Image (tube, rainbow, N blue to C red; front, side):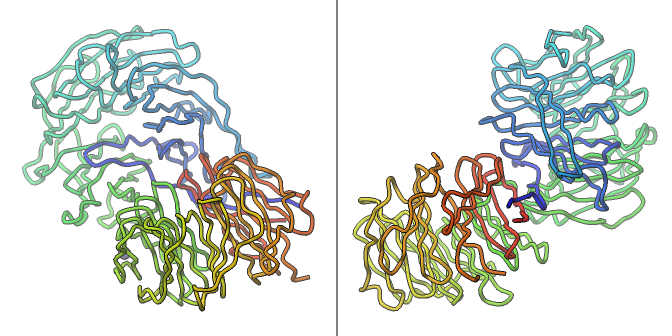
Length: 606
Ligand SMILES: [Zn+2]
């Protein structure tokens, strides 16, 4: 008996309005790396099976939000380096096993380099030296050896935050840091030391957001930022050569990032929802790609060349845009969440995160209709969905059909188009999932922290005495208490599909199973988790007697308990960094999970 990882749907890159998201591409593994939440990710652009794992997730930054992920230049080195807001940098390496289909990640070195958050990282072409940069009190960046951490130079010339850096990928080594107040500094080195400074080519007070030396011998260095200027320096002397401008292509917005396709062409991307391709020599824009400027989400917050003219653009809305030099049309788009997932539906698969974004995977549709946490999702009605959010509304296919007078704490929908909601004002409401109408309601005697709506019952977890009261859907005036309360505040309740039992767990990790009818505990034998329970889902039949029950807790684990054999536990550890939020059975043998880490995972239950 087991559970094995069947598929991983990774989140989109982390984003912030007015801020660049530095991406990284690795030719060898044909994959890109990017930060999202508290984990670093590497996603293989390779569809057709390959020896490269689809996804690699590094959780080593613990509680610190990851800011940047960079591939080591050494082909096949499978090493990467990432930084976080706490100012810590980590060099880690992964491992894969196409067989077990298991990915291992082992840290190799960690360094507390900055007081504040790290903004960018860059390796030397030997994959042994690092330019780390960002913000601090006295230090705005450092130059250190990847294994020891001993200083290999000194970041200087900046008084304000450093935004990006880059190491000329060839000898004689040279470096570049760039940041706030139009500051651009050049270094020389192996022992990188201040060489030259510049505060005349980028407007004072502006933000220079990215810098990058041309591939091969790096004959040039280019910096970009909010003043819409593209400055071109010489890769050796660092002398300003010229601005890259084309009369037929005025830059109408601040630039966020750049990436060289080869030694002559490089891409830029910015607030004017445009992806432009330039030729350093002619200073002419050779190719342009646009998106509707009228939509905030189209601003281009990142970019990275992936070889042979292929370019990947990052939208403020987290979308990944694939383009190719010579082809005026966008090749394909990839959307998804970049915020913890809080609501889940199956057959068809739909997900919602705590920012209110909803994802329809059956049509690759991404919605930004709600503007806050998605409490629940209901797809019972054919080709439609009903969503409830902390933005106090109930929407049906992105359209508002109900405005709550009181915020919806938690909710639960059955299969007959009904949704039971518990509000901040301590009310239990029963809505018609698809019209938004409240057909019946009742004031609860105490705040409620959990709901489970079956075909005929409504089980509510009550904070006062952490008891479970069961309501009759058809008549809220009738109800009964289960003989035994919980240990601590109820966190999640799941009524049996046949309404025989009721599984309810608490914020401490206890999960009691009751017999609904007799309202008596049927077993408290299921193993204590020592962590908040966030999800419980009954496995359906392929016997027919309800037995296996999947559950998830803040501790990141998935525990599939058994009614018949309370001592037997099938488990999957580290399912989702920082906790499992949702759990569903889309197939009698397949589980689907969502986590605080904005990941969605499918599992094969053997
Ligand atoms: Zn929509």
